[PDB]
Image (cartoon, coloured by chain):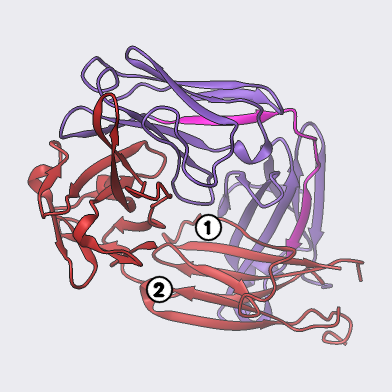
Chain colours: A purple, B red
Amino acid sequence: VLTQPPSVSGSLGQRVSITCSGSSSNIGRWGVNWYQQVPGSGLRTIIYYESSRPSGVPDRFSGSKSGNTATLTISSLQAEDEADYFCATGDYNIAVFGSGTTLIVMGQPKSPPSVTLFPPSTEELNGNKATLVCLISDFYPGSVTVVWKADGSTITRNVETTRASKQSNSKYAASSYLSLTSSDWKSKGSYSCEVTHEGSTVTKTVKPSEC
Amino acid sequence: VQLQESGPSLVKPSQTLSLTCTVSGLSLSDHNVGWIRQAPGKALEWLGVIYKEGDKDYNPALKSRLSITKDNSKSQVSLSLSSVTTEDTATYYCATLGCYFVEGVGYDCTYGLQHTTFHDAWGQGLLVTVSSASTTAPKVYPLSSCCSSSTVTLGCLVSSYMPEPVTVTWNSGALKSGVHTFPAVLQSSGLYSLSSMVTVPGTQTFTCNVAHPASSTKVDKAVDPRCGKHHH
C-alpha cells in the first residue's frame, strides 16, 4: 500500500503539497497518478504518469517524483479544492492505490447557520407517525452541535443528526431528525432545535397545539 | 464517451455481486477497462482489469472471489464478486486503463484516462450494499415551515427507505436555484431518511420528484407553499 498523510491543511492562495511514498518496486519504477474526489461526486483524474494533466484540470495542479516518494502540489488553493486526494501506481502487472489524503482549506469567511425547523405533515400524522426535521445550512467552519428540547427539557433518544457536509456554495450543511409517535407529538406544548456553532446558538421552535 | 455502472444496489451476504459497465461512444476492442471500489470512508481498492484482447489481471487479495468478463458487441464489461460480506459494501467504479508510450522509458498506463485523447474516463460509481434487509420504498411527505417571512422555505421529506440511494429533483429538473438535498441519515428503525429543501424569495408551484431505483418507485409530490390560506 502507498502511504499518504491522512490530512493536510492550507489557506486560500497558499501552496500545499501531498506526499505519496511507496517502494523501489512501484513508485521508483513506474509512473504515479493522482485522483480527486469532492464529497458530492465520484473520482476525477487530475494528473497522470508524473506531471501531465488531463483536459480541463487547472494549471495549479502538478506532480513530481523523487526516488520512491511522489508529490502532488497545488500552487494556489481555492475553495473547490477541498476534497480527498488519492495516488496510484503499478508494481508490474498489479495496480496499488494510496490510503487517501483529506485536503482542508482554511481562511474561508465565517458564516452562522441558517436553521429551519419543519413540523410533521398532516399526511404523516395519519399514519400515527411524526418526524421533526431541523435543516441547517450556510455555516463555516463545517461543525455544529444540535440539541433538541421539548418544554425546555433536553431529549437524547430517537434523535439522529447527520454530520456536516459540503454544499454548493462551499460552506457546510447538516440535518437533524426527531422521530416520535403522533400521540407523543401532541403530548407536549412546544419542541425546539438548538444549533450551536462557534460559541453561538441559533434556536427555532415549533408548537403542535398552535401551529 | 461515457462509462455507466449498473446492477443491484442491494445484495444478500454470501451471494454474488454482479455489475455491468456499459461503455458508450467507444469500442471495447481497443480499450482496457478495469474496476475500482471505495468502501464507506476507506481508501480506493483496485479489483481488476480486462485488457483489449481479453487478458485479465486481478487483485491478489480478491482473486479467488473475482471474475471479470466482457462482450465487445454489447459494449459491456462484467464484474462478479462471490461470497460477499459487509466488508464488500462499497461504491464500485469502472474506468478505462489508458496506456501511452513514454519516449525515454517505455509503456505505462493510467486508470481513468483514455489512451489517445487523454480525457477523463471514470464511471459515475454505483453504491451497492451487502445487507440482509429487504427493499423498502420511501414514503415522501411535504415540508412546510408555516407552523409570513420574506423567503418562504419548503421541502420534501423522503422517509424510511432501504437501500441507498434516492435522487431528488424539483419540477422535472427545471428548478435548481436555491435547492439543497441533504445526505441521508440512518435511524433506529434501520431505514434511511433524507430531506430536500427549497429557499425561494411566490408565484409558482413546487413539486419534488423522488426516485428510488432499488424499489423501481418514482413519486412526484406537490408541496403547498401557501400558509394563511390553507390553514384559514
- In front here: A33 or A39? A33
Which residue does the image show at 70% across and 73% down from the upper left?
A: B175
Residue designated by label 2: B213
**How many numbered discs?**
2
What's the amino acid at mark 2?
A: Pro
Q: Residue visible at 33% across and 52% down?
A: B93
Image coords of residue B41 (percent x, y): 42, 40
Of B142 and B28, nearer the camera is B28
Question: Disc 1 designates what residue?
Answer: B184
Q: CA distance from mark 2 to mark 1?
A: 16 Å
Check contact, mark 2 vs mark 1: CB within 8 A. no
B228 within the magenta span: no
Residue B14: quadrant of the picture: bottom left
Q: Quadrant of residue A143?
A: top right
Q: Against A205, is B48 above or below?
A: above
Q: Is residue A116 magenta?
A: yes
Q: Is residue B60 visible?
A: yes
Q: Give the quarter of the figure containing the N terminus of chain A.
A: top left
The residue positioned 36% from the left and 59% from the top of the image is: B126
Q: Amino acid at mark 1?
A: Ala
Task: Name above or below for residue A37 compared with residue A68.
Answer: below
Q: Position of residue A201 (x, y in %)?
A: 81, 40
Give x and y (percent) for residue B162. Answer: 40, 66
Q: Which mark is residue B83?
A: none
Please say whether residue A151 is visible from this viewpoint: no
| Secondary element type, mark 2 | helix
Q: Looking at this view, is A170 or B214 the one in front? A: A170
Q: Identify whether B151 is placed above or below B88.
A: below
Q: Could you say whether the residue bearing mark 1 is in a helix, strand or loop?
A: loop
Residue lying at the far front of the rendered structure: B103
As displayed, is residue B182 above or below residue B107? below
Residue numbers of the magenta segment? A100-118
